[PDB]
Image (cartoon, coloured by chain):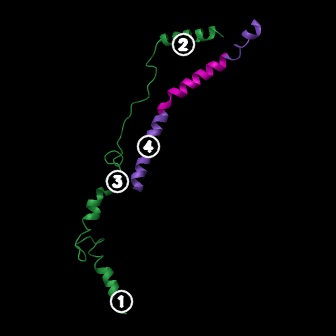
Chain colours: A green, B purple
Amino acid sequence: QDLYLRELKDTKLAPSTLQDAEGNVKPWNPPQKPNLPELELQGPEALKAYTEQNVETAHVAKESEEGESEPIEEDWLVLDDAEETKESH
Amino acid sequence: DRIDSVSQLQNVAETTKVLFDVSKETVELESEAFELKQKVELAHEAKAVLDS
């Protein structure tokens, strides 16, 4: 019937020059051709963390440290504290 | 009483040595855990931007 061609041309003309083909906008004044791929390119970027999580910053954290090559000094300190703890046993 | 108070440091010395070395090495090998943890965080961030 009339609708069988009218609505198909309606949904094949305006959507054609609305997106996918990505050129011009006939039905309504605001264009989404430069809105969804350009202005909304930073949309999720604004929603998410930018320059930290989107770029996955290669934060090279300081490597795990140690006793800094502590000499026998800490050894006899441990000896002394163990001795004074065990003296009252 | 002195005898059965003293008679404990015979078979426990080896246990003390092994526990000391094992605990110290496990504490000081946490570099592997840190590397795995940061890799996990970065993989999670990549997956996060993916579903975003």
Above or below for A46 versus B3: below
Mark 4 — on which chain does it sit? Answer: B
Which image quarter is the N terminus of chain B in? top right
Contact check, label 2 and label 1, Cβ < 8 Å: no
For disc 4, the marked residue is B41
Contact check, label 2 and label 3, Cβ < 8 Å: no
Per the model, the C-alpha gap separating discs 1 and 3 is 42 Å
Say which mark, if any, is on residue A3: 1
Task: Return the disc, 2 or 1, that comes first in the chain's sequence.
Answer: 1
Contact check, label 3 and label 4, Cβ < 8 Å: no
Q: Which residues are magenta?
A: B13-31
Residue A12 % position (x, y): 31, 80
Q: Residue at x 57, y 25 (%)?
A: B23
Per the model, the C-alpha gap separating discs 3 and 4 is 20 Å
For disc 2, the marked residue is A78
Residue B16 % position (x, y): 63, 19
Contact check, label 4 and label 1, Cβ < 8 Å: no
Say which mark, if any, is on residue B10: none
For disc 3, the marked residue is A47
Residue A77 % position (x, y): 51, 11
Per the model, the C-alpha gap separating discs 2 and 1 is 92 Å
